[PDB]
Image (cartoon, rainbow, N blue to C red; front, side, top):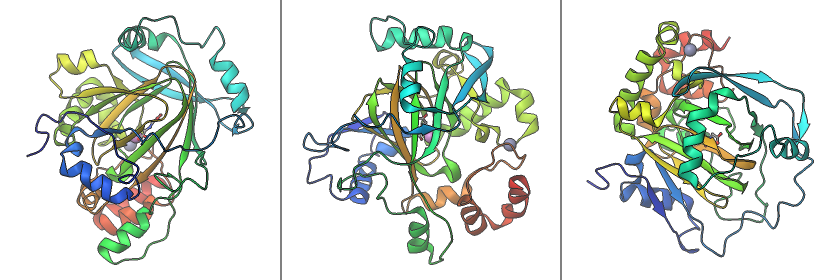
Length: 331
Ligand SMILES: O=C(O)CNC(=O)C(=O)O
Ligand code: NI
Ligand SMILES: [Zn+2]
């Protein structure tokens, strides 16, 4: 078996290898990349997402989210307080202000230490889930707005045609902005391109050990666990690497820099934080190997998770027994 220790693998495709997206995902998996839950892909030197990022300041962040923490430094939840709309230019200025800017630090490890020590004492503001793309339409390789759709994958594999669409989202972050422990909707893949700015540090649990993280989460957030059998779907819970280590949870970490892709694999729990002002673009996708994960994916039915239109068909076709209860949670 390839990659039995479930290490995060890093790939350097040639420009020739960068033509066929599906084929390269399949290649990465042939090398065991999926066992980690997360892989890094460094694009060939000849590739570019777009010409420049000089004209992005007028993009609107309609609902910036202030991420307010509760708990202890290594075990906390965050809720999102809606703030007034601001442009990306205004957001960048805010990110760079004395109140919100990245502190002096020696290296990534030093900054990681500062993050877990001090995160809960601040409430950074995040521009998340903004529908759109920064890929040039003429970028033909690994353009996250031009991927084959999950609906077409399901149709190709299972022969049923379904409604729904599948488009990318932009994320504008600043120092300490945080993504909570989660897997993707329907335990899909995700792919994330860091367009511009400061790094993003990722933590990931191997898919074969996902239930170990779930069990610890139930212990650490007992009220939440009683309220919902799949509360990590709420995407609000954080657990530090120190606490994971103390509890023997297998995981890995890696820092993504501008110009790099990350892929998360089905049922790979991940969490992380941004080092400073940046912009990422991400989208979910599927492969034939995903179908069995989609069939088995946990669902939140307590009403908190509240997801896209397009997830309806996924649950309806892949999980017909769960469909009634789940839909009650969406309505
Ligand atoms: O970048 C973020 O804030 C969160 N991204 C993801 O969880 C992802 O790409 O799957
Ligand atoms: Ni994700
Ligand atoms: Zn729930």
